[PDB]
Amino acid sequence: SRPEPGDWSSPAELAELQRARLPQVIAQALRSPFYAARYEGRTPPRTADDFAGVELTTKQDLRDQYPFGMLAVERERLATYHESSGDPTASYYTQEDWTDLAERFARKWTGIHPSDTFLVRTPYGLVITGHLAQAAGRLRGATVVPGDARSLATPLSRMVRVLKSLDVTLTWCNPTEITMLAAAAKAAGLRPDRDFPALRAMFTAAEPLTEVRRRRLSEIWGGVPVVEEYGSTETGTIAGQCPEGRMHLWADRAVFEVYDPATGELSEAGRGQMVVTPLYRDAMPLLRYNLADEVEVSTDPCPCGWLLPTVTVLGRAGTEHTVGSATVTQQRLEELVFSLPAAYEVMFWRAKAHPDVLHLQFEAPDATREQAAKELGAALDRELGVPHRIEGLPLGTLVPTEALTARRDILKARYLFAEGEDWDKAIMYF
Amino acid sequence: SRPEPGDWSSPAELAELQRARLPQVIAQALRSPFYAARYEGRTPPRTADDFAGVELTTKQDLRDQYPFGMLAVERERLATYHESSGTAGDPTASYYTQEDWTDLAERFARKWTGIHPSDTFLVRTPYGLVITGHLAQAAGRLRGATVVPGDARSLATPLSRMVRVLKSLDVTLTWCNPTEITMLAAAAKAAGLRPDRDFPALRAMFTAAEPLTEVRRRRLSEIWGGVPVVEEYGSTETGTIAGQCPEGRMHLWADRAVFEVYDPATGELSEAGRGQMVVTPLYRDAMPLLRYNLADEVEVSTDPCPCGWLLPTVTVLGRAGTEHTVGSATVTQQRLEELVFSLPAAYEVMFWRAKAHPDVLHLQFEAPDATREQAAKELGAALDRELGVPHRIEGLPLGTLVPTEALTARRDILKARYLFAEGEDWDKA
Ligand SMILES: [Mg+2]
Ligand SMILES: [Mg+2]
Ligand SMILES: [Zn+2]
Ligand SMILES: [Zn+2]
């Protein structure tokens, strides 16, 4: 029996749903070999109050336990198994676990309905991402279109066609992919801001995503809401956006805490690394898993009325470089790039922080490329004051045009060829 | 609801199960725009006896109805949408209600080896729009097996990573096409693992009739230590329509589809015999199909089988059009496949290709230095014996037809990144 919004009236009430669940979570976690060995020969936690002294679990811990070190149920109870790479990180779930995952993804403020046609444009190979959105789509009755991603069967040009031919109403993909699909739509002679009348909402992740960029993504696609969530390949969705544009931690389904690496202290709000304890996760229990994302958590109430804290994802701990006498983050640079007028059509850029200089490149059309570079330079002088070298690049330099238009199909392996057929197509990959 | 084995005791009761269902199938079918237009003005079929006069539905029709010409329910009732791309032109769309999916997953789960909660099931077929990966995954979930979504042609999941998963997770079941069975075996060898010994948990490999001769199927099993290679028959639009029993025969799932044999020389349909495979699914609300011609050449037998499955059997003979003349004989890929995989397993010949010329059959294959020249000579003798065809055979070193990097490259996943440190490589972008 999982709680849903409305089942609590104040922060105190929500904190009690969390505490009444903690002993079940601790006792379940102690059944995995990892926690069993961590507390071997020691007194283990049992009570909601024992939770305050529990040591963090790191991403390195999960890697060290490949494949089933974190398993707390018999394999017969497992529904799916997943991996993410970067030394694989294994995760797995019962079917009851999957109901919690599906409901957390389905908490989209735009809703998901049977009248929806939901294009799932994230990978299905080993990682949970595509499966999660598909599970959520099926839970709410939406028509799921499995686009996959990084799949030779489904290049951008084909997704563009499917978006229009099937009157897709909801999409799921990362924010960089939202601009890739837009670049691909234009290469097909389609306009993302008006030629897709059925599209009503685009779901996406905190790739760290600034509000500047998020609103530009919406405007590229004609003003449709871009609904951001925060999650990881190991946890599924842990926060989702409200209509007021804030991301609310799903604290009715996990205990969230903020970790300070210098002091070693855990805190309920403030700035630090995101630490999570899922409450409905029997197969692979996690006690204070440190996602190692730099976040800021606030308990201020939001005008949307959802009585849950909110979170800002400021990046992965360490993505802060120095040039001249100042700190340069990807987030701050991203704001300046996507503060350029939409008419410049600057979507794709990259930068390298040298000790003496920030090297930034972007591709843009000929008409506005020079003035985009001077304006971006002046924005850097104004906002960061760091020395810089900016190069406007021809279109297709960072994002090849072929990638936007290439068609490619899965063809059945062939062994006997006729004259006029290239038998080099028998050369096998994958 | 839907029948299960044990719900009929004879061919007569099975036929009664089908004919009882046909009227509802017909009325459902005529709700789609395609079948409504086929009968516009004319009187519609209604009874099971009316079914005999129904014209075929073709692959071209399905392609002409892209995307929703065949739809017979409101969009809200659809669970999933799928398409398969052809050589060129439009794709072939298909789509299913949630209840349709129950019939689909039950048909796939009709595996004589079973699918159990104790299983770890590596699904190694594409999830990109086609049904194939979703079908295997739905059946694994129906039967409680731990599903491992390998995907295929996916950039997340190269062969090297599948080999690690097969070994490290003690995978007990796989689903992939027959070429991928040998690709995985070559990748396992490349990683120093013996497909025939080092995977003790693997108990069956499910695969489809990618024109699969018995000679090749037996060698695929032998390569993986003799574990069953369980063939099924279906299409990306139908799902599984027939499955193997332990006797090695493929049994049509006649309790959920009416199957007929089309003879193009007469235009007539039969229950048995040799001809083109026609199928009418009986539990398919969203996209009903009346007498859909797969156009594969098959032979259907009603002779009982000692496995216990009271269902007719089908042999898939191939597809018309693959008629290659060399010298004075005809050469088919299936006959060449039999000769190639008739070589002794110790030669390790798994990958081959051939070009048919009027004056020569040019055949090439991969094999290790130790057995390469002997393989070519035996194969050249085999072509003389069985086909009498002029030939030129070139054995190749490993890595020629299947490049070694395909077998061992690891290719991570990674994320988009925009700001790079002084030392990092920003051509990722
Ligand atoms: Mg299981
Ligand atoms: Mg629907
Ligand atoms: Zn809010
Ligand atoms: Zn049988």
Image (cartoon, coloured by chain):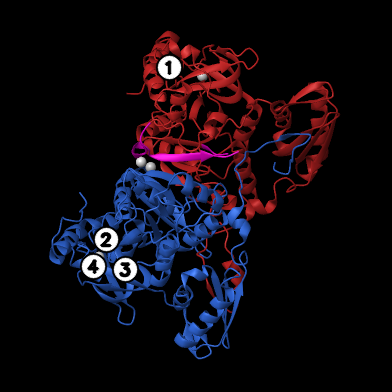
Chain colours: A red, B blue
Instruction: Tell me, for residue B278, which label it has, or none.
Output: 3
Is the residue at mark 3 from the same chain as the one at mark 1? Answer: no
Residue at far top of view? A12
What residue is rendered at 73% in x and 38% in y?
A: A349
Label 3: state its secondary structure.
strand
Question: Closer to the observer: label 2 or label 3?
Answer: 2
Which mark is first along the chain, 3 or 4?
A: 3
What residue is rendered at 54% in x and 50% in y?
A: B154
The answer to if A76 sits in the magenta stretch is yes
Residue at image mark 1:
A44
State the image quarter where residue B251 is shown. bottom left
Question: Closer to the observer: label 4 or label 3?
Answer: 4
Q: Which residues are magenta?
A: A73-89
The residue under label 4 is which amino acid type? Pro
Subunit bearing disc 3: B
Is the residue at mark 1 from the same chain as the one at mark 4? Answer: no
Instruction: Name above or below for residue A285 compared with residue B220.
Output: above
Q: What quarter of the picture does the C terminus of chain A occupy?
A: bottom right
- Say left or right for A345 vs A227: right
